[PDB]
Amino acid sequence: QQVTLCEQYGYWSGNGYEINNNLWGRDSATSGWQCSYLDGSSDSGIQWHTTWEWQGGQHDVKSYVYSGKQFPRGQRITSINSMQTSVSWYYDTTNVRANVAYDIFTAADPNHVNSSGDYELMIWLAKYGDVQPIGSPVGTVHVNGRNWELWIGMNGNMKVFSFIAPSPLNSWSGEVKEFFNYLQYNQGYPAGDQHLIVFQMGTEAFTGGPATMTVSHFSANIY
View 1 (cartoon, rainbow, N blue to C red):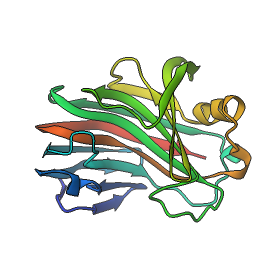
View 2 (cartoon, one colour):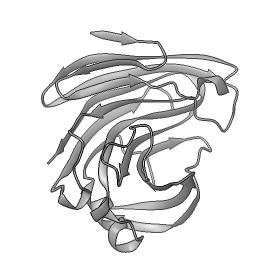
View 3 (cartoon, rainbow, N blue to C red):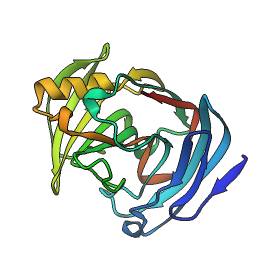
View 4 (cartoon, rainbow, N blue to C red):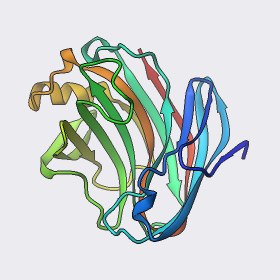
């Protein structure tokens, strides 16, 4: 398809969802391109896909195109009752260096710019090739009925918690409050002083292609 977004930061919004052709790191590449496509949307979720090829800058993310759930600013993490989400996705080739991940920012200032936060929570449903999260792994943790390798890193002032699935999860239904709750009581995360800034699902593309990630369904319910 209904909408095609090939420009850097090309953007679509509808039904409480959005897509951003978020090619933030494209200058790191020696060549390449990427488009994002809206296949359909309703109040209950969005269907979209992205196709890309990127070369050069081996360890650099070229893009994190995403579908975001829209929500009002000002929701304190401990006051949020549910951050339920469901996704089904597939890559047309595994011969890429890329991941599939949720990206979530929180900040003490509820009006923080949406490109960062005081804290970042990532949930990596798949990783292809030798790509690795920021920081270092601290062990396996059991969260929301599944096991994850937890990585902790620092990007400027922002502390980053990345939960990595042990094998690709092409379909996942989760309660993201369980991840914040785990962090609150095991990693010193000050959830009572933090507010939700973004809630996104997408793919970080490093190198390879042409490759397509198709998202058959993405939805979230935040209240």
